[PDB]
Image 1 (cartoon, rainbow, N blue to C red):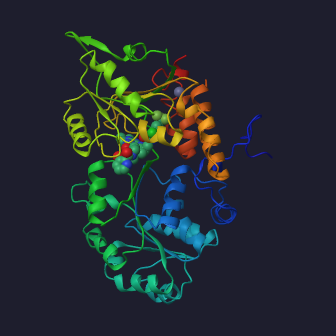
Image 2 (cartoon, rainbow, N blue to C red):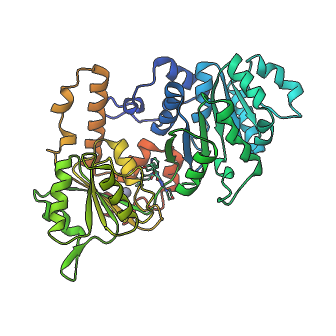
Length: 432
Ligand SMILES: C[C@H]1CC2(CCN(C(=O)c3ncccc3O)CC2)c2c1n(CC(=O)Nc1ccc(C(F)(F)F)cc1Cl)c1nc(N3CCOCC3)nn1c2=O
Ligand SMILES: [Zn+2]
């Protein structure tokens, strides 16, 4: 019988079309053969590609185990070398080793009692994936150095990585000496995994594991407190933003802390100018500004001395602010990936927030003419596909939450979202 009906008339859209660079044919064959999947989710590819091609440290926040294991199991299987998984979760490690064996991936649990059986075979390069406790790993840095020299370690995964922080709710003394991994193995990337989206605990993990410029990702969350809306521009900045404003004592303000993302530096200045006329507490943020001025706006926003930052998408990576009540995209966003990163900064305190896109078909990020100028065929086609996916989202009458979760998240996240989805607080299209 037919197992899916994903194909639609008027589209040749695979999940691979929205990955940069594209997975090659052997990478797809490997994924199918050893993991029984046809495609990578964007976050899975971000982690896998950063490990394989850049040897980059990662902190991967993953709310659940749905789609998690692929990020650290796939790279060593693809290159045919060795990946180490450090975890205190014995039963889960046993379950994953058996699943790998049943997929014809040579994997084992290494510990003191298991060493007589597996250690010689690990040293000779017969295992793709080795699971160890932090206690065992801490007394065997010599072994890891030999495996790096003789085989080459694709990555070290540290699961329950929040256990390294004495400031968290689940501290393990066993994790303390994992700080030595980067000293013993400076060229081996670490993928630190945790379920906690706490910026405080992320900083502790990066410090304690000595991670260098780690790629930070955060997935598996439904974010029921984010309301999504897409609305047409009206041809006038004050006309467009007036609906978001309330008059208080001869000055106007937003409901709460607000970020307005604009495509151009020019537009950030234009929008700031119109809000300044209303004596609204706001500041401009773009790369054309000085280091001190940018640093000042950051601190002032964090201290609630300004209510609104009008910014390019240069603003956001350095802000851990939990009470962002409103994100406005003033102009179509660059693509769905950037849009996802930007709306994800809203309502991290878990209270009701709104994310509005104000767009016109004439917006710079819907202009195909700028993309036709791209002479690299592969990059041109990717940029056109990303613009088309963004345009399809903006134009849609379907649930905005369903579109975003379908693209970025494991299907399990959609099952958790069925409560918020279709209600008055989900999105503009669910309210109608
Ligand atoms: C988007 C990612 C990336 C980011 C962290 C990385 N980042 C940086 O700037 C950054 N980079 C480097 C260093 C430090 C940094 O801050 C951008 C923001 C982040 C994400 N998420 C996930 C998410 O929101 N998914 C999500 C789910 C549903 C919906 C929808 F459709 F229903 F509306 C939309 C989206 Cl986008 C996330 N989720 C929670 N929460 C989960 C629930 O508890 C509260 C925190 N926080 N959070 C995040 O911070
Ligand atoms: Zn909806």
